[PDB]
Each structure stands twice: as structure tokens, then as C-alpha cells.
Image: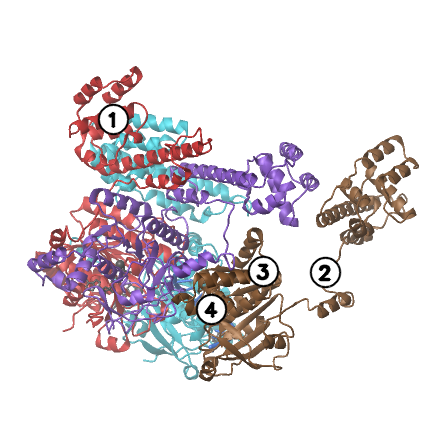
Chain colours: A purple, B brown, C red, D cyan, E blue
Amino acid sequence: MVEIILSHLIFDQAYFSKVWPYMDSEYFESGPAKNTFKLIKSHVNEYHSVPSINALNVALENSSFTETEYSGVKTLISKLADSPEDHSWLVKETEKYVQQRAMFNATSKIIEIQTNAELPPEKRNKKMPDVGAIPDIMRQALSISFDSYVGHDWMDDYEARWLSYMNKARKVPFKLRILNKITKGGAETGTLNVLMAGVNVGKSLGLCSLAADYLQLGHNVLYISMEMAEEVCAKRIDANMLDVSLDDIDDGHISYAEYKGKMEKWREKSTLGRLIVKQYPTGGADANTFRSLLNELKLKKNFVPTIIIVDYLGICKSCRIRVYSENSYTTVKAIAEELRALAVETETVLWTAAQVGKQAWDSSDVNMSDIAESAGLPATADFMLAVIETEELAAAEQQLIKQIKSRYGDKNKWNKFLMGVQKGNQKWVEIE
Amino acid sequence: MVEIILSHLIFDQAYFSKVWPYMDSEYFESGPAKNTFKLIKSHVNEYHSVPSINALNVALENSSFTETEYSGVKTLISKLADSPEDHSWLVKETEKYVQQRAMFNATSKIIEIQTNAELPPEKRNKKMPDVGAIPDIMRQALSISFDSYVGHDWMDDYEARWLSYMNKARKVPFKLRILNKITKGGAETGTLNVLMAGVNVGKSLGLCSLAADYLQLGHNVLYISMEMAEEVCAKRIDANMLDVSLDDIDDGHISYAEYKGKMEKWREKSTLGRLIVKQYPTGGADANTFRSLLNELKLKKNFVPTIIIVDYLGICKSCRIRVYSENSYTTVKAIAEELRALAVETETVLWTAAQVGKQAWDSSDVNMSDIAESAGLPATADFMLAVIETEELAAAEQQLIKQIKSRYGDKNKWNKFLMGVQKGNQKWVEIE
Amino acid sequence: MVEIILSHLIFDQAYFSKVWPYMDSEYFESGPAKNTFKLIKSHVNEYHSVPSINALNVALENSSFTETEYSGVKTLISKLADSPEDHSWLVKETEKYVQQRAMFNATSKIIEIQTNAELPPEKRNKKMPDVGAIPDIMRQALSISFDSYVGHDWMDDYEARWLSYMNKARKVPFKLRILNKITKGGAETGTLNVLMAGVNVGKSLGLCSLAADYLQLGHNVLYISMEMAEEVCAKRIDANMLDVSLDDIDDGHISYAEYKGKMEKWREKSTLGRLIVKQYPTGGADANTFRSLLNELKLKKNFVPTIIIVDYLGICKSCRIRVYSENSYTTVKAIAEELRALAVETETVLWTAAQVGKQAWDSSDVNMSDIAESAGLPATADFMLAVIETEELAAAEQQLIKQIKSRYGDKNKWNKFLMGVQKGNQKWVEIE
Amino acid sequence: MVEIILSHLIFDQAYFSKVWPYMDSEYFESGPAKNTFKLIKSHVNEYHSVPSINALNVALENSSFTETEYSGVKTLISKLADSPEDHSWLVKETEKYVQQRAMFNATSKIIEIQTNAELPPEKRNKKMPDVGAIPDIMRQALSISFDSYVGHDWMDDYEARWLSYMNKARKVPFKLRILNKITKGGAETGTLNVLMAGVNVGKSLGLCSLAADYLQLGHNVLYISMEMAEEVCAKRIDANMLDVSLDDIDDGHISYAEYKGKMEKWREKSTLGRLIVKQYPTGGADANTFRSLLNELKLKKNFVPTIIIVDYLGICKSCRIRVYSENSYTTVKAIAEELRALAVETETVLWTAAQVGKQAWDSSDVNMSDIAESAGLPATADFMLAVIETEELAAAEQQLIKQIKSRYGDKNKWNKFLMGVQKGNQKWVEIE
DNA sequence: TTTTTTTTTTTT
Ligand SMILES: Nc1ncnc2c1ncn2[C@@H]1O[C@H](COP(=O)(O)OP(=O)(O)OP(O)(O)=S)[C@@H](O)[C@H]1O
Ligand SMILES: Nc1ncnc2c1ncn2[C@@H]1O[C@H](COP(=O)(O)OP(=O)(O)OP(O)(O)=S)[C@@H](O)[C@H]1O
Ligand SMILES: Nc1ncnc2c1ncn2[C@@H]1O[C@H](COP(=O)(O)OP(=O)(O)OP(O)(O)=S)[C@@H](O)[C@H]1O
Ligand SMILES: [Mg+2]
Ligand SMILES: [Mg+2]
Ligand SMILES: [Mg+2]
């Protein structure tokens, strides 16, 4: 019903006020319709008013159109008329038409993406999204509607604000009381949590400490390690939970009898979850691979995680961008968005560990202008912490957390606090 | 376009009074259009009024034209309608048509001058202007504009300027008597105004107080927050407007009945504006994202603001610098310039806040030299109010407001004044 | 490649044990391929074993098909052979085929959903899902990778993990007691180890000392020089092994007999290994050249090196990135990743040097931030030691070695230790 | 015999091991042969194994070339079949075929370069090499003989190594005793030695003194000046050799009789080489230019230098990086590496000058970190000497030479000694 | 959009 839409854009005002901000040139066929809409949009952009028939016939004459295009536009303009109908069926019909056009465009785009992917390298188009980006596009098209929320309107959105006042989101508590204090009860389900740190300063130590703490609380924890072997991460967890140093395990100070006894003592406890460590090669795993892993864990082991942990965000595959196509910032932002989408879909608290820039290394204080790969990670993330064990905290067997971005509470309340990192047992103890 | 021009010369008054002095016979054609315009001009010269269709036909009957000219003029006269187009588009389009025709005539004239110049000197026309007159002729073609407004012309716009001083066309009052006293009637449109907060003063309390005061005066306020969510800023706004303490909302002392009653009481009042709160991540909002936000609000929400309040200048990002620093002087200077450019181009009062220098923190008196942003903020800021909160003032629930830069009026007239800050309701009350 | 898939399903148990878990009739075709796979699936369901050609033909006789389908199935069944192709290529190709067929089916399904949505509610089928099911449908078709391994469990696999604790075959001792002490048993196979210092401090001296120490332990050492000639580095190795001097070799203080005697005495030792020195022009080699060099070395001589020393990573040339395609942070990190991949493929200890920026060329200490090339090298590295020499140290002939990145052990247990570097002999001497 | 080569690449493991490392895509054809080899090479790079006929067919079906190419590749693959053969006839025939194809490609590229250089500029299709590197390409066409040198074995090849210590043909002695003492016999051929002084401290006086000293010791010296005329450098050499001050030549205190007598007295001495001075405009000479100069010197003037001197490397042009494309670091490092490559190619002692940073000027000490244009120059230079002059040293007619990078010996020993530079005679004298 | 060299400048 393109002709009706154009006719009521020209000859009606309430319809124009209701539907114009959502109309786009891509919703019209490449014939007379798109060119007529181009003329209307140019006139509105230049004069901030709805053009008349004379205005468009003047705009058509002052246009660089071929004979076929000129004839089609003139015929379409001649065919326009103000058919009296109701301003409740027109709006819904226009919304349906726009949604259908958006779905059609998305389908064509994903077909083109799949055709582009199968092409051999050095011939395939670049900057075109890969196959893994197909669902996201299909998520955007279904979101088209003639209702748009731009900002929070005082006196117009106050019931929702009162609900936000009275209601509080559910929280997965930590085992460290300081994190609960700074997060008002823990972390929410569909979140992307990042623990940035320098190189060789405790990115995996903190993640393994969190994994052990969550495992002792009865959660199903999935540790996806992209840099370390499964046995290494499981040895970190064992050191955390069996109270044996990594030096003792490697040197063989502990015997198999004591190890088995401690493992069985932990097994007999009812307040214990299941921790599963999966190793992927560097750059060999993405969000879709994680979803396949979750599906096989559910089907073959009856395992549904809650505390999915990714060792390093910067190593994982983009899943939306082809490898070595965009810059580090865009690729890491895409990875963060994909991981947060996975966390929201699976209702799992997702924890990761990015790397800070070379400047932040051995720096007593860090800020958001220290992230190495991408500064867009805080925007995508829901809670971001830092590690500041630079020069003298190591001698005192301590650490420091900056709280760069905390969406659960206020970052400027307990911004910097001291953590008792114990590297032999790979754990965090509190200074209290 | 000529048909529209002639029709709206015949059947309009404002268009005629606006475009008649810039209308010439040579601008139309060498056929029916020129003859019709000659008839119109002859009628308006003999009778100083716009001719009617019957009078035009009578003049055409009593005129010296051949058969083809008679047919063309009759058809064109029969093809003129009193249709109603918008005035701005009509004036702009007829101006463009006149300019194009004048340029074509001048180019043809200079080509004819050049052709006559390359002719035997014994054999040439004397009336044709010499070649040296070519640059001037084109100038007369370029000096064709229905309305000349290039800047403010002294001695030529003194009557309009006086209407600005009497009507205070630029001032926006403050709702606080002291702030109106030192600004000679409030802040001005197209200005950047900042608050300098010493140690122990919040930057968002004063901004929320100003936003509430503007809201109570009927102004559309756009509050862009960086370090806080939309709900938190709107909660500060509610605290100030509903007289409820900030902690009372979190505790639950105020019930839904009182909240809704107060909100509907405010909604009943016709002297209330609209407040739109938009949240952006730290460092993820330059003064080009604000332009997009304004465009979206105007197109979708029809919300065109008169007050724009940015939560914190330091948290913002300089679009030109691109690189971002937590506390760098070059970025603050660029951010201030970009925000003031936005205020000027949008004709809105723009408010922001900054932290004073550490020396300014310790000293109750704050010097422009004692500012974290030196030569960057006291150079791009029309007004820079300084807020001092010492122990004695806090014990008395007061803050010392000092005026550090006042483009509006004399800085030393009323430099120091005590403000009744309420930290619970986030409000500024005057002191007798 | 349906014929290959079916042939290796029937005639290969290893292929059947990794692909049958993930296989459906929708993946193959709508003609003879689907019918053949349906026969195979029916036979394996009725009898839990892979069918044979005779059994498949008997089942085809028992099953009922139309004439065309019967002929197609007979023709396809006739075309099955063992054809022992590579397992890795076969599984990768069948994974690709399954993924592409699943994507095609998902696209057709969403197109059918969209077509059914446009139908009137009376005409539309209730079995097809709504448009809201379009995204997840496209997502479940992107999570069909072939991977049955779920990973460690920490409670169901602690016996295997303890057995893995006893697998110390990855460790390679250092011949220096301090290095073994700080590495908890020496370096590990398939790791990128770096020895960084300033210009003219002894990086190649340390590399040659490590080469000699590994040679005296019976290892095969491959020294790849990027600046010096083969005979020059071999002179340093001779100075380390024969233990006379560098100048005495060039000053004639060693007669040919003594040289012959010492070389033959070292030949008589059964604890000595093999050392090959290879030189490359600056910026002309990487793992691609190194892999061909490894293959040529293995073919020409019974030499599979356990230790691979690269004179400098920076002088090396990246495989994919051109000579000056991108900046240092990229291509240097790319070369580091390629070298680590080569080491983990060959299961060899990889040693290389790194340069330090000018800021730490005359400093008593050097940090990880003082890496002249990309900071991604101290991300792919595993044991990045650092060599610091001052005037006081050079007076005592004692270079200081600082533990910069220690992945094997605790980086701060023995952070700084003094060595006994003898520059004339190109040897590192432990200090007791 | 491309079919045989491909067939035995497929059906012969022994053949593939030797021929593959050398096979390249530019040795077969522009049609079916190249496409088949590209398929095989892609399969080998993806799976590290020789593809089978089924694998080749599968890759052919998943390929994007047209119908003609597809049919040609299919026919070629169908024609591939193993035949009873012998390893030797095949390896020798393959070597002959590869050499012939390399020669054919080389001569085609030579013709293309000749027909491209004979074109008007700005239309010469840049990125094509100039005529200067016409023979070098041919030299690459002859260095393909299936006989890659694996490397040098420490124990297997030590008689050849020992017959390189008393040879001493690599070292070229100085004339000053201190420089010989610190370098333990003088500089070595195929090296890059550098003087760092600053601006107007020396650094060309030292180069001229070295040139004169080498010339007196029966050497052919090639001075290359990028910033001075051929007569200024020759005047400096005349002042050095004839023991006549530059002021005396300027002021005419030396007669033609004395000049002629001294020149003839030098000529009649047998212990004297030939010095040739060549001038190039600043930034208008590179390694290829120097090689062309060497060739034309050998042919036209039968002059074979051994002590090639370049006045300043920083003033030369890189032969690989486009001008002003990369920063100073990369460009200067590349220039120094190319100069060292030239020196090792022609087996000459290469001497050069380098500037220091602005901070090192008028300083009593110059460190290695004070190098001006690149930190890579010290890393890619065999020997560097820093020339330091203060007011006290200038008043004493002495300069302090500090050993900054001493690759021929220990720099800690004799790090700073005082030369007796005489600026009038452009000569260095010792103080011993 | 980050990254790294070198320089030059300026601000604190
Ligand atoms: N086997 C070990 N025994 C004792 N301490 C260890 C051992 N391995 C590592 N550590 C310590 O643990 C610290 C943190 O190491 P990681 O957990 O790997 O941090 P990291 O950020 O993951 O390092 P990356 O991934 O290489 S950037 C190191 O700095 C060491 O001090
Ligand atoms: N014609 C001359 N007569 C006498 N002394 C001279 C003459 N030319 C140069 N000198 C001296 O030689 C010193 C060093 O000369 P150079 O070798 O040209 O210095 P330089 O470092 O090569 O110059 P740049 O900046 O590198 S091009 C100067 O400082 C003068 O004292
Ligand atoms: N022929 C020699 N005789 C004695 N000492 C030497 C000799 N060559 C080098 N040295 C010493 O070796 C030290 C550093 O050796 P190098 O291996 O050259 O250091 P490096 O520059 O980091 O390694 P490169 O650049 O890859 S050769 C110097 O400071 C000298 O003291
Ligand atoms: Mg880690
Ligand atoms: Mg070096
Ligand atoms: Mg000079």
C-alpha cells in the first residue's frame, strides 16, 4: 500500500506526524515509489513541512531522473489522492507494511551474507558481516515499530520509575562480602562482568577464585579457558579448594591418598555444584561455539551453567566479524556484545578478564583510558574491575581494585579497596 | 514554476509584497509567460493593485498581440489557480528561479559581448558594452537575493536591536532572586554556563536544582547524564519537586498514593515544562551525539529544548580530540568549545559543572588561577559560578557561591553570596 | 560430497564414531541421498551396528520406493568404496557440509514463516511458528559444530588430573640451578620464552649460553641467526664449550692441536647433542620458512631439534602481514603468535630475544612496559626474563636478571638474581 | 611435464618431500595447471597433507572459477595417475623444469620492466621496479637448484670453521693504534660502523681522516657525500694527506710547486690506494644507487672499493619504503639494514655518520639513547663511536671518543679515550 | 579506533 502511504503523507497531517519519523527509503520498491519518497524526504529536510503536489512536480522537473524514472514518478504523483479513511487502521496497516519490508530486507541481506561467505578468500567482499551475524540482523528487523523511546520523560514515565524504586532485581551473591557490599547483593543474571588487569598480575587468579567461590555455593560453573590447558585451570581450582599450594602439587609434597581424601570430603558435601573446564585454541572459539558447548552439556551431561567464565575476551573469535577484517576496537566490542547476548539468552552470570594497556602496567592508578584492545568494552559491560598490584602490593601479598564501571551500585563509594591475593592457593582473602 | 509564480502574484498578498520589487520581465521567457507578466506589470503600473482574472482577460482583449500570442496568453491565464502553497517554500523557490534566470541572461550577455568584440572594429554595435564590463555584469547577476540578512548591521538594525533590549529577548530567568540579580535578568541563550565545585560539593545537586527551577518556569529541559542512570537523576528531580527527601524514597516512607497525588497535582498546573533525561556511558558522548539526540527528540518526541544540562564536563568526550583522558586539559578546552558551539547553534542555555583546583579545594576563596581547568574553562564560559562548602557552612546548611567569571555583568558587583543548600531534597533556597 | 560421507559411514568405524551423533535426513538431499541415509538410519536403529552393502541392498529390497527413487538408490548404493582419505580433512569437510546444509534449511524455514505470516489468519497454518521465532531458528543452525568433548569436571576426573600432575615430560631442565629453581623444573615444550635487554647488553650471549647448556645435556639445538654469520655464532659456541676465550681464538693463543683435542674430547662424550646454526637475511623468515627448514633438516639428517633459538623476533618477518603493511603492535604480535604456534606444533622450547626502548637503555631496572616492539609479545610469551647491566655490575662482571613474565612459577619469589656473565667466554655463570 | 609433477606430488610421498619446499605457483601455467596447483597448495596449507583425488574433486566443486576453468581442472585431475618411475629422473627433470620456468618468468619480467620504464612519467604504472634491478632479478633466476643449505653443524663442520680464524682476511686494520686495540685488529668486512657526534662537532672530519688512513694503507676508498660537494671532501683529504691547513689553501699560503711536489711524492709511493669521491643530492641515493655506482666503477674505472664510506645514512633514501610513508624509526632502520646488506654483499667495510638528538648537543656526555632518528640503528650496526667535544676539549684540540656499541670487543674496556683531532688539517692523532 | 616510535611544545 505504498500509494496510500504517500497519499496520506502528503494530504494528511496527523498521519504524517505519527508515521514520518519511522519511515525510511529502504521500505519502498526501487521503482517510482522510492524516488517519490526521496523527493518528499528532501523537501521535508529542506523546508520542514509536508510538500504539496505542485512542490513535488517542481522538484521532479528539477531532478536528475531518466525518462523511465521521470515518467513513473509523474504517473505516481498523478495517481495520488486523499481517500477518506480512519486514523486507526492507517497507522496499524503502515506499521505492518514497514515490518514486512524490514523482514524482507533482512532476509535478502542474510542471503547475500551466506552467498558472500562461501566465496574463496581474496575474492570475497570485505567489511560484510560473517554468517554468525545473521541472527542479530533478524533481531533488529523484528524490533521495528512506530513507538520509539528516546529518553526518560518526567511526568510521562513515572509509574515505571516508581516500580524501579520499589522493586529490586534478583542478585547471585558472591562469597566475598566486600563484593556484595560494592554490588548491593551480588551480580544479576544477564550481565557481562569484566576483571581487567595487566599481564601476569592475576587475571586468571581472580577468575579462578570467583569460580571456586561460586562452586562452593552450589552453582554450576563453566570455565572456558582460551589460553591455558584444562588441567592447569583445574589445578588452580584444586589449590583454591584443597588448601594446597601449587608448589606442593608440582613438587609432589601431597600424596594421592590425601588428595583423594580431600576430594571425597568435598564430594560428600551437599552444598557443592559442578565445575566443567573446557579449553579452546586461541582464536578458535566464539559465541556460537559456546552455545554448541552448552547444548552438548545439557544433552549429554544434564548440565546447565549459571556462572559461565571466559578466561580472556581478547583471544576469542568475533563471531560477527571475519578474522583480521576490522580493527581491535571494533572486534573486541563485537565480542563483548556477543558474549553479553549469550549471557542474557542463557540467564548466566558471565565473567571475563580483559587486558589493560602498556601504560597501565606498573601504574598505581588506572582509569577507563587504559584499556588496550577496546574502550567500548565498558559501554557493553555491566560491571568492570581492575587489578593494581604494581610494585609494593606484591611484597605485602595484596592487591587493589579500581571499580572502573559498576552498574550494580555507585563506583565512587568504595572505589579503591585492598584485596589479599594469595598466589600459592590462587585465592582472594579479605583484609578485614 | 512560472505558472505558480504568476498564479501567486495574482492570488496572494504577502507573496506579492515580498517578491514584486525583485521581479523583472526578462526573468520569465520570450513567449506566453513574458506577455502575461507584461500585462500584469502594465495593470499594476496603471492601477496600483493586483489585477483579477477578468481584468487580465479584458487587458488581453485590448492589447496588441498576434494569433499565436493571443492563444498562448489565453491558455496561460486560464491555467492559473488560487491554490494555497506554504509561503517559505514559495519565496525560496521563486528566488532560486529568479537567480537561475538572471545568471543565464548574464552569461548570454557576456558571450554576446565577446562575440561582438571579435568583429571588424569598423563593423560592430556601439550599444554593446565593452569587454571590460564583463566582470561587473556577472556581479549584478550574483547580487540578486529576495532578502539580504548577512549579520547585524549597525545603524541599519537599531530599531530591532532596541526591541531586543526592552523585551530581554535573550535572557532566561533563574527563579532565584540572587542569581537574577547578578545576571541582570538570568542567563542568555546560546551560552555555556558552568559550576565549579570545591572539595565536599556535589556537581549534580546544583544542576538538578537548576533543572527543577527551569521545569517549574515552563522550560523544556534536556538532562544528559554520564555517571548516573535516568532513574537516579529523575529521582533527584522528584526529591526537589515533590519535597520528598531522597532517602525517604529508598526507605519507603512515602507511599504510592502520596507520590501519585503530588505528580498529578504538578501535572494539573499549566506552568510546568517537560524534562527528558538521557543517559550515556562515561566518555561515550561527545558534542555530536547530543546533536543526534536533539534531532531524534525533535523528529520523534517533538521535544525541542530550551535548556540543556550536561551532568559533568570532564566525563564528556571531545569529538575533535577523539583520544580520551580521565583528567586532561586539552580535552576539557575542546569539550567546552564544542558544547558552547552546540548552545549557539541550538539557541539553548547550556549548563555543566567542573571540579575546582586542589588549592581551590583547601582555600574557601577560589581564584580563576586556582581552577583544575585553567585558560580552558575561563575562556569558553559565559558564566562560571563557584560553590564553596566549608565545615561552618555545612553545619548551617549553606554553601558560599562565588562569581569567578561573568560575561553577563560585572563580576565584582555581587561576588560572594550564601546559598541555602538542602542535600536531602537536592534544592537551593535563598537566604534572607 | 554426500557419496563420500555415506561411503565412510558404511566403511569406516572411526568416521562413524564422530559424525553419526550429529546427522539428520534433512542434511543430505530430497532424492536418492536422503533415501540412502534413511535406510542406513533404519538399519542402525533396528540393529545397533553399521550396515554392509549386501545388508543395505537387502533392506532396500524390503523397503518400498517408487521406480525413480528405487533406481536412484540402487545407483547411489553401487557407488560406495573404502577410499581411505585423511580423517582430519574428512571430519572438517563433513562439518562444513552439515553447517551449510543447516543454514540453507534454516533460511528456507524462515522464508516459509514469513510467507505464512502474510497470509490471512483463516488461511495460515498454525503449525508454522510466528515471526518471533526467526532469530533463534537461525541461531540453532549456527551451533551444529562437531564436538562431543565437554571438558574436565574436577570431581569426575580428579584421578586423571592427578595422573597428569605426574606427567613431567613437558619440562626441560636448564643446566643452571637458579633457572630451574625459578621455573619449577625448567622450561616447557611448546612455549615462547624471551630474553630481553638493551642494545649491546648480551642477548645473543645469553642465547648462545642457553644453546651450549642444552647441547651439553644431550638436546638437539637449532640456532637461527638473523644478524650474525654462521661462523661468528659458532665461534661464540666454541668459546663457551672449549672455554678459552673470544680474543684468544682471534689472537692465535690456541694452536690447531689443542682445538682438535678439545673438539675430539667433546665428540667422545655421549651426553652431547647436535647443534645446527642457520642464518637468514634481516626481515626474510618466519615459521613458514622455519617449517620448511625443519622438514629439510629432518630429511637430510637425523635431526629433530628439541630447542629452537631465534636470534631476534623483531628481525623476523610475519607470515600474513607484509613487510610494512601495519604498525609494530600488530606484525610483532603476529610473529610472536606464529612462533608460539610453531613451538607448540613441534613441541619444542622456543627461545628468542627482544629489544628494549631507549627509555631503559641506561636504567638500573627494566619493566615489562619497556618493550621496544609490540606489547603483544609480553602476552604470547611464557618466561620473559630481562637482562640489566650497570657500571657497578660490569665492574663485577655480574649482569642482573629480573623475572619479568613468569608463567611457570611465582614471578616474585626470586625477582632479581645476579648472574656471573663472562663476556670473553660468552657464558653465564651461576653465583653461590 | 606438469601432469607428471602434479601426479607425483599426489601419489608419491618421497617425491613430495624434496620438490614441495621449492614448488611455487608461478612455475606451471596460466590455466588448468596453475588452478590445480593452487587447489593442492590450499589443501596442504589447510591440512598439512597431500590431497587425494576425492579431496581435489571436492575442492574443485567448492571453487568459484568459470566453466572453462572448471572443465580444464576436471580433465587435468582425471588425467592424474601414478606411473612406475624412479626418484632420480623425476627430481632432475623437475629441477630442469623449475629452472626453465624461473628463467622464463625472469626474462618476461625484464621485458616488462624495460617496456614500462620507456614510458612518460606519472603514467609509468608505479610499484614496478626500475631498470637498475634488472640483473639482480636474473641472479634470483639462477639461484634455484633444489639444494637449499640446511645450515652449519658445530661438530660435523669444524675444520672449515677453524680455517677461518687465522685467515684474518675479514678484518681490515686501522692506522691509529687505539682503534685497532679496541677493535682487536680493526674493522671487519660486511659491517656497518657509525660515528655519532652531533652538529658541527666532527663526524665528517672523522670520516675523512678514516678515508685518508685507509688510503695510505693501500686501500681503494669510495667516499659518498650526500650533503657536500666532491671538491670540499677532496679538499679535506688534501689537507689531511699533504699536512697543509684548510686555511692555508683558502688564504693561498701554498704554491703550485709545493702542491705538485707533494702529490707526485704521494703518487710514487707504492703503499697508496685510490680514493674516489661521489656526490649525490640529499635524499636521492639508496642501496640500489650504490650498487649501480659500484657496477659502473668496476666497469668504467676498474675500481673495486673495500672501504666504502657514506657521509650520512639519515640523508639517504630507503630503496623499499616510499618516501615519507613510515616514521623516522622504521625508515632509518630500513636504510641501515639495506646499507649493511650492501656491505655484506660487496664485502666492504662500510662507515657512516649519525646525528644525535637535540638534548645531547653541548653536553659533556652522549649516551646511546641520544641517537636521533631511530633506536633501530644501534641494533643494526656492528660498531658505533660517539664523538664528544666540550669547551675545555676544544681548547685542548682534543675530542673524547666513547665506545657506544662495540661488537668487535668489550666496550667497558677503554670506553672513553681522548683523540687529538686537529680541525685545521682534518686529522685524528693519538695521544699515546 | 589503538599502537608505536621521534620530536616539539606546553602545562603544571
Ligand atoms: N605455578 C605457579 N606457582 C605459583 N605462582 C604462579 C604459578 N603460575 C603463575 N603464578 C603467579 O600467578 C600470577 C598471575 O598469573 P595469571 O593467572 O596467568 O595471570 P594472567 O593475567 O592470566 O597472565 P597472562 O594470561 O599470561 S596475561 C603470576 O604473576 C605469578 O606470580
Ligand atoms: N673549512 C674549514 N676550515 C676550518 N675548520 C673547518 C672547516 N670546515 C669545518 N671546520 C671545522 O670542523 C668542525 C666539524 O666539521 P664537520 O665535519 O663538517 O662537522 P659535521 O658534523 O660533519 O657537520 P654536519 O652537521 O654533520 S653536516 C667544525 O665545527 C669546524 O670547527
Ligand atoms: N668479540 C668480542 N670479544 C669480547 N667481547 C665481545 C665480543 N663481541 C661482543 N662482546 C661483548 O658482548 C656484549 C654483548 O654481546 P651481544 O650478543 O652483541 O649483545 P646483543 O647486541 O644484545 O646481541 P646481538 O645484537 O644479537 S649480536 C658486548 O657488550 C661486549 O662486551
Ligand atoms: Mg591467564
Ligand atoms: Mg644488539
Ligand atoms: Mg657533516
- Amino acid at circle 2: Val
* Viewer-nearest of discs 2 and 4: 4
Q: Which residue is mark 4?
A: B244
| Ligand 4 within 8 Å of the CB at mark 1 | no
Residue D278 appears in the picture as rendered: no
Q: Position of residue C377 (x, y in %)?
A: 31, 59
Q: Position of residue D64 (x, y in %)?
A: 39, 33
Helix, strand or loop under label 3: loop
- Amino acid at circle 4: Val
Q: Which residue is mark 2?
A: B150
Is the same chain shared between marks 1 and 3?
A: no
Which one is in front, C216 or B48?
Answer: B48
Q: CA distance from mark 3 to mark 2?
A: 27 Å
Q: Which residue is mark 3?
A: B305
Q: Position of residue B239 (x, y in %)?
A: 48, 68
- Amino acid at circle 1: Lys
Question: Mark 1 packing: few (<14 Cα in 10 Å), some, or many (20+)?
Answer: some
Q: Which residue is mark 1?
A: C38
Lower position in the chain sequence, tag 4 or tag 3: 4
Q: Chain of mark 4?
A: B
